[PDB]
Length: 304
Ligand SMILES: N=C(N)NCCC[C@H](NS(N)(=O)=O)C(=O)O
Ligand SMILES: [Zn+2]
Ligand SMILES: [Zn+2]
Image 1 (cartoon, rainbow, N blue to C red):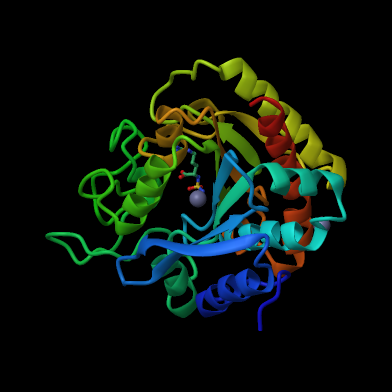
Image 2 (cartoon, rainbow, N blue to C red):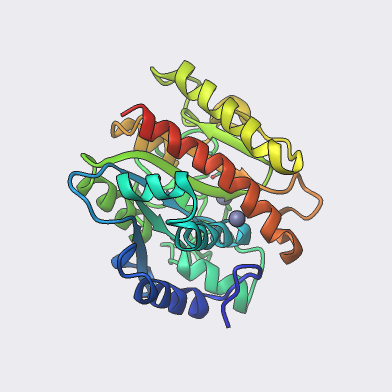
């Protein structure tokens, strides 16, 4: 049984992608953008009412296997779209005018592994030459100052960059999709945990994007909007100085493709529970996060 207020295993999320699509044909379609190392279909939901020449926002969750609140959030976003479409003015406008691509779990193989073997797994589950150590950090595997700062060359390490940029089937699949849809995708949102942040480029070097002032102001406003609900405090800014320098991330890569609004979200908490955020916090976390995501969406829609 699927529930939006619990963490759902992959079999359940997969079945949910099929069911939520079938139940909402005028709002949702489903495709597979590729397969994981283990051969699992990487599902993508396109959320929006059909219309001509629609811009798009792309959002993924579940890069990192143990960040279960991320996976829960993508599901919550779709929950909100289907529940409130027609009833609530902003969500209705968003879905009438834009498409949202929601990739509920990128690193499916790692997610399954966190359910079956090791709750604290981070990386993919692919093999590495010359060692029995498993996996690549998908957020160190993009062509963005690849494998320099904040990324490890050691396959046994948690920030292993991989054998080459896009070596992983999952990150190749994501990069291919974004490249193939570059003319329509106006914003890229990538959901992680924890530490309560809205981050924008750059992380791969200490340098700033040309629209730094715009991104800074937008992140600042989205943080303030998030805080209105429960008082949850987020920090914000360029990744390198706001969290740490780290190369090969998808946010920086997407920005360097020309996607001008590119954000990494770090959801709750600030370390009390860390990755093992209790299910009792799913609702509040997702509801406040919705406010920030909708704020960014409204900004994008209003500044085309
Ligand atoms: N480093 C880039 N490009 N963006 C920020 C990503 C932050 C993210 N933090 S986490 N979820 O603790 O692993 C990461 O290090 O990949
Ligand atoms: Zn993460
Ligand atoms: Zn709600």
